[PDB]
Image (cartoon, rainbow, N blue to C red):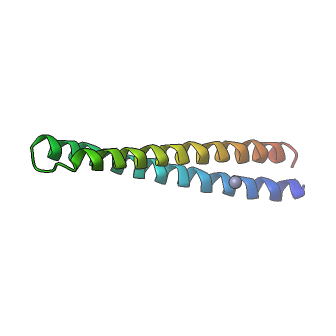
Amino acid sequence: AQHYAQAIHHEGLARHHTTVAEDHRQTANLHDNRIKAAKARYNAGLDPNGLTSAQKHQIERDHHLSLAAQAERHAATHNREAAYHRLHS
Ligand SMILES: [Zn+2]
């Protein structure tokens, strides 16, 4: 049960990735609010560049969602490997 040690390793790595995923989702949502603000400026006649800015915040939002999903997938991978080793401790 070097198994125990591998379980703890993989569990900590899973937690890491879970936190990275949560941070990315939070970042995505911060971008999502700026999309909204940008469009509202544009539409109120205060910022002709506001649609361009909204588009860039969409790119950023979507990139952060994609990095979140990837982190979540890595977390799942480590959790399966952790469970395996726990079962064999
Ligand atoms: Zn990993």
Give the camera-side residue of 13 and 28.
28
Residue visible at 49% across and 50% down in the picture: 22
Residue lying farthest to the left in this orientation: 45
In the rendered structure, the answer to whether residue 67 lies left or right of residue 45 reads right
* Residue 3 image position (x, y, % from top left): 86, 53
Query: Which quadrant of the figure contains the N terminus?
Result: bottom right
* Residue 33 image position (x, y, % from top left): 29, 46
Residue visible at 37% across and 44% down in the picture: 58
Q: In this view, does 5 lie above or below 41?
A: below
Residue visible at 48% across and 44% down in the picture: 65
Q: In this view, does 66 lie above or below 27?
A: above
Residue visible at 54% across and 48% down in the picture: 67
In the rendered structure, the answer to whether residue 72 lies left or right of residue 89 reads left
* Residue 15 image position (x, y, % from top left): 62, 53
Give the camera-side residue of 2 and 66.
66
User: In which quadrant of this rendering is ligand 1 seen?
Assistant: bottom right
Residue lying farthest to the right in this orientation: 1
In the rendered structure, the answer to whether residue 83 lies left or right of residue 40 reads right
